[PDB]
Image (spheres, coloured by chain):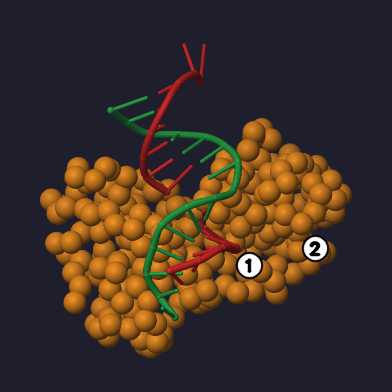
Chain colours: A orange, B red, C green
Amino acid sequence: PELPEVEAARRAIEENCLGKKIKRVIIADDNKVIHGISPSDFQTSILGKTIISARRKGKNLWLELDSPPFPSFQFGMAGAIYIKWPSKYSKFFVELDDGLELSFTDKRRFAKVRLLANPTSVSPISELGPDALLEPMTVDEFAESLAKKKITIKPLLLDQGYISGIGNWIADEVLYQARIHPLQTASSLSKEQCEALHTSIKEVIEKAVEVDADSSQFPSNWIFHNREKKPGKAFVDGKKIDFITAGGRTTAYVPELQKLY
DNA sequence: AGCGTCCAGTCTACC
DNA sequence: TGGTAGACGTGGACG
């Protein structure tokens, strides 16, 4: 999940779970996902504490507790949060003093759950670039840095180091909206296009958050809705969609609108 | 469920 | 450079 999906989970927890003691904990005995601590230790630790606030940066979320260390989640490809089994794919589970349950699942096992004294000072959050939703580069700045990069525009957007939060489909959507080929070099962008990408990134990510990442509420005219179709049968507003790879990720774009020099 | 194949955010080996 | 080609477990969609 990309920024919208995580931001939705953060808001949901900030709304239903703050100020309640953790009465019961269950940590999946998953050597790969539960990173740097035994599910047992991890359990004993947070037991009895209270969530003081839910924080986020990029595709990362952590729970600030009334006392460290704090549990953090790097979603990966299939990470997800649930409030209300323990589901089969649950890796982190807690029942609060009011019967409310919170669970982090990962049906694919590509996520990372850690228990760090300060997630903000260490990987992966420490190397994260400014957040797309919390620290949006001003129009001028955005471009200014777009210049200093001799990299393809998309893989540039998929780099958590540069900017954090954007994912494969959010990248495609914004480039499409701003009518910019994914392979156009960063530095070779016009201060006109740079202001165009800047504006779509904002429209796309906000609306996405605004709808709690519920893809079905996504503007009908977003390429997103047809990026699932197979090559040769994928279209948007009559225009044809092409599937090329960039940054090692299948990239959907429309040659008739997204061109390059 | 039962088949088989393909598509789907890190993180490292390499030209 | 930065470009890439693969690896990593495994569910879900589909011929």
Front residue of A207/A187: it is: A187
Locate residue A170, reporting x and y percent: 38, 60
Can residue A202 be seen in this snapshot?
no
Q: CA distance from mark 1 to mark 2?
A: 16 Å
Front residue of B3/A103: it is: B3
- Quick check: A219 left or right of A116? left
Q: Image point 85% across, 54% down: which residue?
A: A45
Crowd class of label 1 (few under 14; some 14 to 19; many from 20; radius 10 Å): some
Picture quadrant of residue A98: top right
Image disc number at residue A124: 1
Residues at marks 1 and 2, common chain? yes
Residue type at tag 2:
Pro
Q: Image point 44% across, 66% down: which residue?
A: A158
Locate residue A250, reporting x and y percent: 35, 54
Dot 2: element: loop
Crowd class of label 2 (few under 14; some 14 to 19; many from 20; radius 10 Å): some
Chain ID, mark 1: A
Question: Above or below — where is A183 with respect to A37?
Answer: below
Dot 1: element: loop
Picture quadrant of residue A62: bottom right
